Amino acid sequence: IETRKIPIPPHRMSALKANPLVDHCKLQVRMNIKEKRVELRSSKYTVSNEALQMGADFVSAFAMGFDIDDAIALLRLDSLYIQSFDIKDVRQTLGPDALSRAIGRIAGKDGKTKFAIENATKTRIVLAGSKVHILGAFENIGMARESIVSLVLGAQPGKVYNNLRIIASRMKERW
RNA sequence: AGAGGAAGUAGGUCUCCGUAGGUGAACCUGCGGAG
Protein backbone atom coordinates (compact mmCIF):
# COMPACT_ATOMS: atom_id res chain seq x y z
CA ILE A 1 0.00 0.00 0.00
CA GLU A 2 1.53 3.26 -1.19
CA THR A 3 0.65 6.94 -1.29
CA ARG A 4 1.88 9.84 -3.41
CA LYS A 5 1.46 13.52 -2.57
CA ILE A 6 1.75 16.26 -5.18
CA PRO A 7 2.02 20.06 -4.90
CA ILE A 8 0.01 22.23 -7.26
CA PRO A 9 0.40 25.72 -8.74
CA PRO A 10 -1.93 28.47 -7.52
CA HIS A 11 -3.07 29.04 -11.11
CA ARG A 12 -5.13 25.93 -11.83
CA MET A 13 -6.88 25.75 -8.47
CA SER A 14 -10.40 26.58 -9.65
CA ALA A 15 -10.09 23.92 -12.34
CA LEU A 16 -8.82 21.52 -9.68
CA LYS A 17 -11.93 22.30 -7.67
CA ALA A 18 -13.83 21.38 -10.81
CA ASN A 19 -14.12 17.59 -10.76
CA PRO A 20 -13.78 11.32 -10.24
CA LEU A 21 -10.37 9.66 -10.13
CA VAL A 22 -11.53 7.16 -7.52
CA ASP A 23 -13.99 5.97 -10.17
CA HIS A 24 -11.28 6.04 -12.81
CA CYS A 25 -8.51 4.03 -11.17
CA LYS A 26 -9.91 2.92 -7.76
CA LEU A 27 -7.49 5.01 -5.73
CA GLN A 28 -8.63 7.20 -2.85
CA VAL A 29 -7.82 10.90 -3.15
CA ARG A 30 -7.59 13.71 -0.67
CA MET A 31 -7.10 17.29 -1.77
CA ASN A 32 -6.00 20.45 0.00
CA ILE A 33 -5.19 23.31 -2.38
CA LYS A 34 -4.23 25.53 0.57
CA GLU A 35 -1.21 23.41 1.42
CA LYS A 36 -1.13 22.82 -2.37
CA ARG A 37 -1.11 19.07 -1.78
CA VAL A 38 -3.10 16.28 -3.37
CA GLU A 39 -2.88 12.86 -1.74
CA LEU A 40 -3.24 9.67 -3.77
CA ARG A 41 -3.60 6.58 -1.58
CA SER A 42 -3.72 2.99 -2.81
CA SER A 43 -6.78 1.16 -1.51
CA LYS A 44 -7.42 -2.58 -1.64
CA TYR A 45 -9.03 -1.97 -5.04
CA THR A 46 -5.97 -0.13 -6.31
CA VAL A 47 -3.88 -2.82 -7.93
CA SER A 48 -0.92 -1.41 -9.81
CA ASN A 49 2.10 0.83 -9.45
CA GLU A 50 1.21 1.56 -13.07
CA ALA A 51 -2.13 2.98 -11.89
CA LEU A 52 -0.53 5.05 -9.13
CA GLN A 53 2.12 6.41 -11.49
CA MET A 54 -0.37 7.29 -14.21
CA GLY A 55 -2.64 9.06 -11.74
CA ALA A 56 0.40 10.97 -10.49
CA ASP A 57 1.63 11.87 -13.98
CA PHE A 58 -1.90 12.89 -14.93
CA VAL A 59 -2.49 15.20 -11.99
CA SER A 60 0.96 16.70 -12.51
CA ALA A 61 0.17 17.38 -16.16
CA PHE A 62 -3.20 18.92 -15.38
CA ALA A 63 -1.47 21.06 -12.79
CA MET A 64 1.33 21.91 -15.23
CA GLY A 65 -1.29 23.45 -17.44
CA PHE A 66 -3.16 21.10 -19.75
CA ASP A 67 -6.87 20.66 -19.31
CA ILE A 68 -9.16 17.76 -18.53
CA ASP A 69 -9.47 16.58 -22.11
CA ASP A 70 -5.86 15.91 -23.08
CA ALA A 71 -5.42 15.10 -19.38
CA ILE A 72 -7.81 12.14 -19.47
CA ALA A 73 -6.28 11.39 -22.84
CA LEU A 74 -2.96 10.99 -21.03
CA LEU A 75 -4.85 8.93 -18.48
CA ARG A 76 -6.27 6.65 -21.14
CA LEU A 77 -3.23 6.22 -23.41
CA ASP A 78 -0.18 4.71 -21.72
CA SER A 79 1.76 5.45 -24.90
CA LEU A 80 1.54 9.19 -24.32
CA TYR A 81 4.46 11.09 -22.84
CA ILE A 82 5.19 14.45 -21.28
CA GLN A 83 8.23 16.68 -21.41
CA SER A 84 9.04 19.96 -19.67
CA PHE A 85 11.40 22.15 -21.66
CA ASP A 86 13.00 25.32 -20.35
CA ILE A 87 14.02 28.05 -22.76
CA LYS A 88 17.13 28.48 -20.61
CA ASP A 89 18.47 25.19 -21.92
CA VAL A 90 21.01 25.13 -24.70
CA ARG A 91 21.24 28.72 -25.78
CA GLN A 92 22.47 30.29 -29.00
CA THR A 93 23.15 33.80 -27.67
CA LEU A 94 23.97 35.18 -24.25
CA GLY A 95 21.83 38.28 -24.83
CA PRO A 96 18.88 38.64 -22.42
CA ASP A 97 16.48 39.59 -25.17
CA ALA A 98 15.78 35.88 -25.03
CA LEU A 99 12.35 35.37 -23.53
CA SER A 100 10.30 38.09 -25.21
CA ARG A 101 11.58 37.69 -28.76
CA ALA A 102 11.75 33.90 -28.54
CA ILE A 103 8.25 33.26 -27.24
CA GLY A 104 6.87 35.88 -29.59
CA ARG A 105 8.40 33.79 -32.36
CA ILE A 106 6.92 30.67 -30.76
CA ALA A 107 3.31 31.76 -30.38
CA GLY A 108 2.88 34.31 -33.10
CA LYS A 109 -0.14 36.55 -32.79
CA ASP A 110 -3.25 34.60 -31.72
CA GLY A 111 -1.19 31.42 -31.39
CA LYS A 112 -1.18 30.91 -35.16
CA THR A 113 2.28 29.38 -35.27
CA LYS A 114 1.96 27.14 -32.25
CA PHE A 115 -1.47 25.98 -33.39
CA ALA A 116 -0.22 25.21 -36.89
CA ILE A 117 2.48 23.17 -35.19
CA GLU A 118 -0.18 21.38 -33.16
CA ASN A 119 -2.31 20.50 -36.14
CA ALA A 120 0.84 19.38 -37.92
CA THR A 121 2.63 17.12 -35.49
CA LYS A 122 -0.39 15.92 -33.50
CA THR A 123 0.96 16.92 -30.09
CA ARG A 124 -0.37 19.13 -27.34
CA ILE A 125 1.82 21.87 -25.88
CA VAL A 126 1.40 24.78 -23.51
CA LEU A 127 3.58 27.89 -23.43
CA ALA A 128 4.25 29.88 -20.26
CA GLY A 129 7.43 31.96 -20.29
CA SER A 130 10.58 29.94 -19.68
CA LYS A 131 8.80 26.60 -19.64
CA VAL A 132 6.98 24.88 -22.44
CA HIS A 133 5.18 21.64 -21.72
CA ILE A 134 4.69 19.07 -24.46
CA LEU A 135 2.34 16.10 -24.51
CA GLY A 136 1.87 13.14 -26.80
CA ALA A 137 3.93 10.44 -28.42
CA PHE A 138 7.65 11.05 -27.98
CA GLU A 139 8.58 11.09 -31.65
CA ASN A 140 6.10 13.87 -32.33
CA ILE A 141 7.47 15.48 -29.19
CA GLY A 142 10.95 15.25 -30.67
CA MET A 143 9.85 16.75 -33.96
CA ALA A 144 8.27 19.64 -32.06
CA ARG A 145 11.47 19.85 -30.02
CA GLU A 146 13.65 20.20 -33.09
CA SER A 147 11.16 22.67 -34.53
CA ILE A 148 11.24 24.87 -31.48
CA VAL A 149 15.00 24.78 -31.04
CA SER A 150 15.36 25.79 -34.67
CA LEU A 151 12.77 28.54 -34.12
CA VAL A 152 14.66 29.93 -31.14
CA LEU A 153 17.78 29.59 -33.24
CA GLY A 154 15.83 32.02 -35.38
CA ALA A 155 14.85 30.12 -38.53
CA GLN A 156 12.03 31.45 -40.66
CA PRO A 157 8.74 30.12 -39.24
CA GLY A 158 7.27 29.20 -42.61
CA LYS A 159 10.47 27.43 -43.63
CA VAL A 160 10.78 25.36 -40.48
CA TYR A 161 7.04 24.77 -40.65
CA ASN A 162 7.37 23.35 -44.16
CA ASN A 163 10.21 21.10 -43.11
CA LEU A 164 8.14 20.04 -40.13
CA ARG A 165 5.23 19.25 -42.40
CA ILE A 166 7.22 17.04 -44.68
CA ILE A 167 9.05 15.30 -41.86
CA ALA A 168 5.81 14.63 -40.03
CA SER A 169 4.40 13.25 -43.27
CA ARG A 170 7.23 10.82 -43.75
CA MET A 171 6.95 9.86 -40.11
CA LYS A 172 3.22 9.28 -40.52
CA GLU A 173 3.91 7.08 -43.51
CA ARG A 174 4.52 3.44 -42.68
CA TRP A 175 6.44 2.34 -45.70
C1' A B 1 -2.50 79.59 -99.73
C1' G B 2 -2.24 75.28 -105.01
C1' A B 3 -3.08 70.97 -107.80
C1' G B 4 0.90 68.73 -110.15
C1' G B 5 6.43 66.59 -111.05
C1' A B 6 10.34 63.72 -108.72
C1' A B 7 12.80 60.73 -104.53
C1' G B 8 13.62 58.36 -99.86
C1' U B 9 12.00 56.25 -95.39
C1' A B 10 7.90 52.22 -93.03
C1' G B 11 4.88 37.63 -35.33
C1' G B 12 3.78 37.33 -26.93
C1' U B 13 -0.45 32.48 -27.19
C1' C B 14 -2.46 30.35 -22.34
C1' U B 15 -3.09 30.77 -16.91
C1' C B 16 -2.70 33.87 -12.65
C1' C B 17 -2.20 38.62 -10.45
C1' G B 18 -2.38 44.27 -9.71
C1' U B 19 -4.95 48.27 -12.26
C1' A B 20 -8.92 51.85 -15.01
C1' G B 21 -13.78 51.77 -17.27
C1' G B 22 -18.21 48.98 -18.47
C1' U B 23 -23.84 46.59 -15.57
C1' G B 24 -23.52 44.88 -11.40
C1' A B 25 -21.25 38.95 -7.19
C1' A B 26 -19.38 36.98 -11.23
C1' C B 27 -18.27 38.88 -15.98
C1' C B 28 -16.18 42.02 -20.40
C1' U B 29 -12.68 45.48 -22.19
C1' G B 30 -7.89 47.94 -21.96
C1' C B 31 -3.10 48.71 -19.24
C1' G B 32 0.97 46.91 -16.26
C1' G B 33 3.57 42.65 -13.88
C1' A B 34 4.65 37.14 -12.82
C1' G B 35 4.56 32.08 -14.35
Image (cartoon, coloured by chain):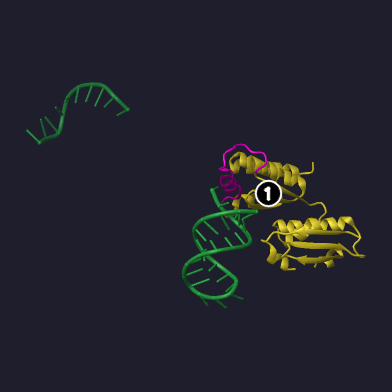
Chain colours: A yellow, B green
| Residue B12 coordinates in the image, percent (x, y) | 56, 52
In front: A29, or A35? A35
SS state under label 1: helix
Tell me which residue sits at (80%, 66%) in the image.
A30
| Residue A62 coordinates in the image, percent (x, y) | 73, 59
Left or right: residue A77 compared with residue A142: right
In front: A17, or B8? A17
Q: Is residue A29 above or below residue A148?
A: below
Tell me which residue sits at (69%, 64%) in the image.
A13
In front: A17, or A76? A17
Task: Pick the quarter of the image with the C terminus of chain A.
Answer: top right
* Residue under numbered circle 1: A120
Q: Is residue A98 above or below residue A11?
A: above
Chain identifier of the residue bearing label 1 in the image: A
| Mark 1 Cα-neighbour bin, 10 Å: few <14, some 14–19, many ≥20 | some
The amino acid on which the numbered mark 1 sits, given as a three-letter code, is Ala
